[PDB]
Length: 318
Length: 71
Ligand SMILES: CCCCCCCC/C=C\CCCCCCCC(=O)O[C@H](COC(=O)CCCCCCC/C=C/CCCCCCCC)COP(=O)(O)OCCN
Image 1 (spheres, rainbow over the protein chains, first blue to last red):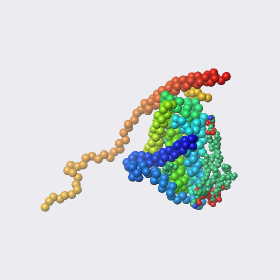
Image 2: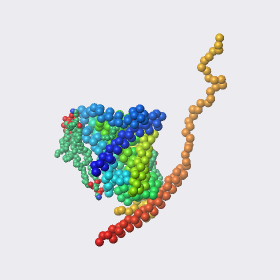
Image 3: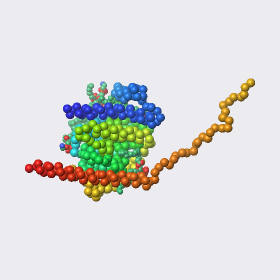
Image 4: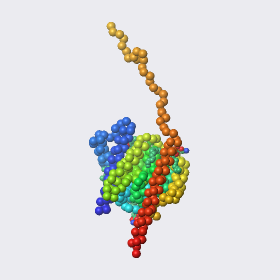
C-alpha cells in the first residue's frame, strides 16, 4: 500500500512535468504575440505526448570519445534525484515524515549537481566541459547564501520539520515577516535550477547546448524531465516556506488546492521571468551572489537570530 | 482625356508622426516603498510574536500532560 502511494506521487509529477512544457510554450508564445502549440490535439493538449513518443523512439548515440559508464549514469542520477526530492513535501501530509526534511532536501540538491558535472565530463566534448565548469561556478556562487537564507527563515519555525511550517504560518504568511530574504531566496532558486537569467550550464546562444550537447533521444528527455521536475518542486517548496495555506485536519483537500494553486503561480512567475530578461554572465552571477546577496544575508541572519530573543518570540520544539 | 492620376499625399498633408522617446516616470518615491516594506515587517513581527507565545504555552501544556502520564 506504500508502493501505491509512491506511484501516485511519482507518475502524476511526470504527467505534470510533461504538461508544464506545453504551458511554457504557450505562455512564451502569448507573451511574444504568438499562440504556441495549438494544432496537436485541442489547444495543443497532445503535444507533450507527441514529444515524448518522438524522443523515446529516436536513436540514441554513444560518442566515440565518451566515457560510457558515467555517460549513462548521469541522467539516471538526475531523474532519480528529481523524483526523490518530492517525498518529504507536506501536501499537507508527507510521504516520508522526517525530523530534518530541509537538510535532506539541501543534501539531495547538492548531490543533483553531479549529474550535470559527470554528463559534461563524460561527454568528452569542449562545449560540454565548458557547461560543466559553469555548473561548478554556479554552485559555488549560490550555495552558501541559499543555506544561510534557509537557516534565517527557519529560525522562526523552531525546527527543520517541513510540516511544522504549516503551524508556523497558521495566521499570517511568513513572507510578511521575511519579505527581503524571500526575494533573495527566489533568486537563489532561479540559480539553483539553472533557469533564466541564470541558464548558463546549457547556455544555448553561447555553448550550443552546453553540458547536454552530446545527449540525444531518451537520456536527453530524462535530463529535461529532471530539470522541469526540479522547477516545480522548488516552487512548491517556496510556496510551503513563504505562503502558508491554512490546513483543516478534516478537510485536507482545501490545503492541497491552495498549495497547488500557489505552486502554479510561482512556476508561471518563473516562465514570465524567462520571457522578460536577458542572460547574466557567469562571473557576474558570482559577483552578485558574493558582493550583494551574501552581506545582506549575513546581516539578516544576525537580525533574525536577535529578533526572537528581543521580543520573547522563540518557537517551541527544541 | 482624363486627369493624371498617381499615388500622392492628400491635399494639405499627413498628420504628425511621433518619433521621440516616450518612457514615462510612473513610479512612487523611495521613501514610500521603504515605509511600506518596514510597516509590513513590523506587522508580521507583531503577529508572529503573539503566535509564538501561544505556541510556547501549548507546548508547556502538552509537556505537563506527558509529565502526568509518566509514572
Ligand atoms: C527595522 C529593521 C528591519 C530590517 C531591515 C529590512 C529592510 C531591508 C532593506 C533592503 C532590502 C533589499 C532586499 C533585496 C536584496 C538584494 C537587492 C539588490 O540590491 O541586488 C541587486 C541586484 O538584484 C537583482 O537585480 C536580481 C537579478 C535577478 C532578476 C531575476 C528576476 C527578478 C525577480 C522579479 C520578481 C521578484 C519576486 C521575489 C519574491 C517572490 C516571492 C517568493 C544588486 O545588484 P546590482 O544592482 O547590479 O548592483 C551591484 C553593485 N552595487
